[PDB]
Image (tube, rainbow, N blue to C red):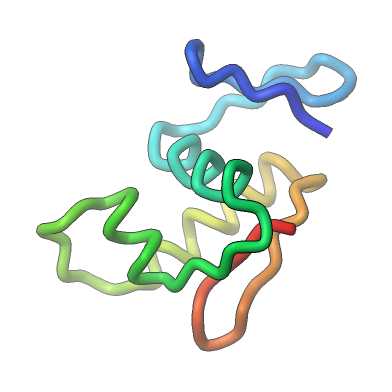
Length: 88
């Protein structure tokens, strides 16, 4: 339902509306779309999006996912309760 330009870091919906993701939102999108079905824990996402020296709340991951899903409601992201997220 989306055209994802990984060079321009832009997303276009099926009608050609531009969807502007932040850099972390785009990184998260790439984790999902190239690994469909894979269960990502919150820590897994943190290490790949925030890096190796972040020790704060994992609720930043939940926030990032919600922002991505509000910007891209047709994405088949699913919450894995108590664990993390996957995209089908």
